[PDB]
Length: 561
Image 1 (tube, rainbow, N blue to C red):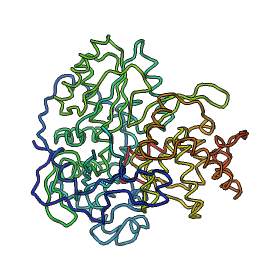
Image 2 (cartoon, helix red, strand yellow):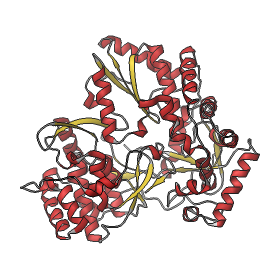
Image 3 (spheres, rainbow, N blue to C red):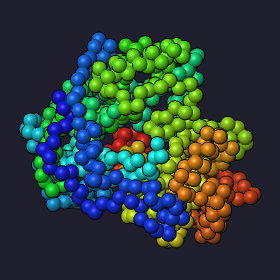
Image 4 (spheres, rainbow, N blue to C red):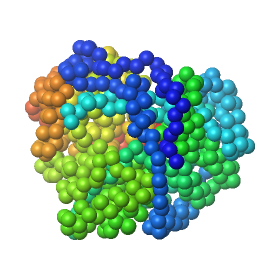
């Protein structure tokens, strides 16, 4: 079947769209080549639609059947429950897209009678009708990038049901997202990990092999490769858990009416097309992708003769570390792996390549690198090319962003030279000038939404990354070259200039005393001649972030404070 069919009606914008970074002194202080930074818009929506529309031919085999059997048995060990109305409403992001039925996320979170009554009606309808397709809206995502000299990306398409239904999805399936992926694939489930824990996983996988070989598998348009049969198989796995009857009913109904497919409408209410693949904007997008990617990949390893594979799966993102069988053998085996995945309906975008140096292996755009700590010992940490984070940071400096990305990048990538020298310096300067340092901000991390104050950063970073995160130095040539290159490409000041600026930002923060001074002392210890001795923060001991990433369920309409 075709992933999508289209009526010919346009994919229309909801709000005003801008294609290019504004010319503005605030953003200009971060990067000067504003023409290189663009935002995807509906203008490219039809082009994306064409790319993601194709025929899926799926042929499963005995390798696939055997993995699925194991997975269903593992799922039977899980016990899960419905979430209450209250619980589901409190997981709704404050800026979640409003309902067509006359209420918004504000009303959901405050449990207003109108909203709660509506959701109760949607739930009742799910239990009573297991067949009528649920309408979805399709929109072009507005996301910011830098041009790639290798021109502009087409907008990603988001397909999602009404706010009333999204709350119901949580009641039916949220508890499952918290328990099922771990039960089925254990340590291979990537969304349960902080950046430091992802680093540890990868280092351990690498070190376990006598002769390690790694690859990342880039599926071409993963959501589009997900078949109706894949989605009903996902249902079978969710329902292998021990659940109340009401949960079985709601999950079957959501599967048949929403997850397996349905009609898409544009923002104008015109019928736009029909989907027969993964919806990009449902609660189960990440969990579903993770499980389905895992079954297909583990099965493909077996068919391909990939030896002792250790996999890290984050939605559609897949890394496999295994025992090298020799250079030529690895290349042949990776081709066999790709052929198997293709039969399973997961053909590659860029073909995988055997990699023999862990620093160069990317998982979710990120890689492990190494630096030195305060006492000169080697310390590993997670990093990534800073181009997109910095381009988005510039945009978000000058355009209202109710859910920003920069605060998530600072938190996730706190130990990195670029988040510290560039992002922290820039934003503490902006926030002090606006006098909004103490205000809580919503931000994305792993596709889920969180809320913290910039003044919370030292405690958060210590808790997630350790005190060393304020003291790393002597980064690798790969990392230094990459960062310097990205800054030059963007027309951003070089790292040395950020250090000049940071001395002033640090001084300003310290002059304020209190929590702001703690930020100056801890976050900018790298920018002072005589380093202060940094000691554990009392604040950090009051934080339990152990399931902070798990609760995000790998992304979606999910919010945590």
